[PDB]
Image (cartoon, rainbow, N blue to C red):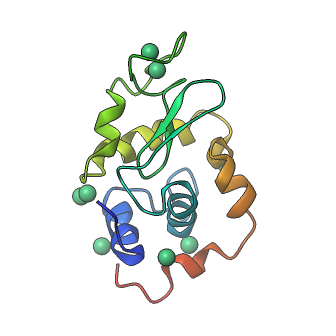
Amino acid sequence: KVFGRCELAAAMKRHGLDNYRGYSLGNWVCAAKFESNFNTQATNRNTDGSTDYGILQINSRWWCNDGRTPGSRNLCNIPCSALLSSDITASVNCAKKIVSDGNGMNAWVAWRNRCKGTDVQAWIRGCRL
Ligand SMILES: [Cl-]
Ligand SMILES: [Cl-]
Ligand SMILES: [Cl-]
Ligand SMILES: [Cl-]
Ligand SMILES: [Cl-]
Ligand SMILES: [Cu+2]
Ligand SMILES: [Cu+2]
Ligand code: NA
């Protein structure tokens, strides 16, 4: 599923991301845009051989099992394929664990390099949520 901007903002809000660990909704929308272009089916291989999955590009190195990431963990206790569903529940719940891990949204390098410090409210501007 490729979400529209405001449709994903509304969904992430419904799923409890707005101000989660202090990160306003536009932070999550901005991260999703640059991670996945709002595509739940997005996959990208990392240099180390792990892969990132779904709207928020959750890495198999730590968070999900894909059967091909040596020495990795599965801290969200989910197959990585679950992260590609049109239903964002698994992605959101796993993201909650990630952002609570100590470095907040800096876990998402694209968030750090492209969203942090910027006017992230622009991502939800005009949206019926
Ligand atoms: Cl957009
Ligand atoms: Cl915001
Ligand atoms: Cl594995
Ligand atoms: Cl959903
Ligand atoms: Cl924080
Ligand atoms: Cu929902
Ligand atoms: Cu809503
Ligand atoms: Na893994």
Q: Which image quarter is the N terminus in?
A: bottom left
**Image quadrant of ligand 7?**
bottom left
Q: How many marks?
A: 0
Q: Is 86 placed above or below 100 here?
A: below
- How far across and down, in percent of the image, does residue 19 sit? 51, 60
User: On the image, which quarter does residue 99 sit in?
Assistant: top right
16 left or right of 97 in image? left
- How far across and down, in percent of the image, does residue 79 sit? 32, 27
- Frontmost residue, 37 versus 126: 37
Residue located 24% across and 52% down the image: 87
- How far across and down, in percent of the image, does residue 58 sit? 49, 39
Residue located 64% across and 41% down the image: 107
Q: Which image quarter is the C terminus in?
A: bottom left
112 left or right of 15 in image? right
Residue located 30% across and 51% down the image: 88
- How far across and down, in percent of the image, does residue 7 sit? 33, 73
Residue located 39% across and 23% down the image: 66
40 left or right of 117 in image? left
